[PDB]
Image (cartoon, rainbow over all chains, first blue to last red):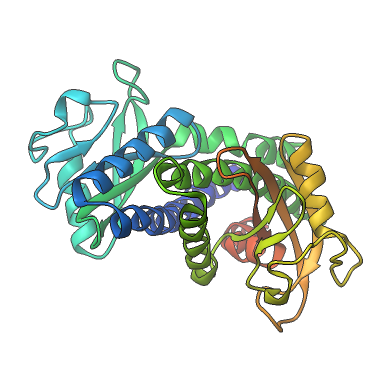
Length: 162
Length: 165
């Protein structure tokens, strides 16, 4: 029991670090767009790319806000796009956009809250790593769901139990 | 404890294999945004400039890229191989690693296991590659990781299991 708890916690901490790395490499990727296309086109390319990531339904799901907290990308909550998210709350009462901004102002960090995986779905616990990308002038958040981390680690868990 | 640690390590490596497949998919999706609008030479130069930056990060993954025929397009560890056929390239442990990339890609994606330095002139160490043929770019793209790095990333988990004993 104690072993499984510390294992699960360690797997979550590892994923936190993975998200900071993935955010860095995603930034470096979209910088190609910004170097070579006009600003409006580069942003469109970034958000089309992030849609494709989310549509993959894999390790991470992106959320993007501007430095003032205007939501730029969030397919779970499409009606929020283009509006201030400063007063947006998750169902567990977290001002998730404020969290993104607070983490970014510190040079990167984490926000913890519940949200569905898709619009209208069951809410579940997740976390976001957010960072301010100087080139795009976007606060980019890579996010993962604890259910998915557990799924990915299920074979490890079953081996330890065996 | 020993059997525990063994099955744990093996499981962590298997997890990383899956991670590499996913990261390759999202990297392909990223580069496609400009393959769709620029000429091949320009788009390829951009993709490989990006991949240089990934490798320079010295983090989870390092890229290697070859063409469908095994010409090496990108490998900062082995810069003299770039622009040459890699079909007879052998790792220090005797693996035809480019042949491995291509055989894995022919199957729809897969793995190649070999020893290689982390940088040009470094000590060789054990690694693996996930490779996949990206039809849009017409490149065989390999995301790679070193076992030493996986172990480093998992050290706090290992120490926690050890403390519980």
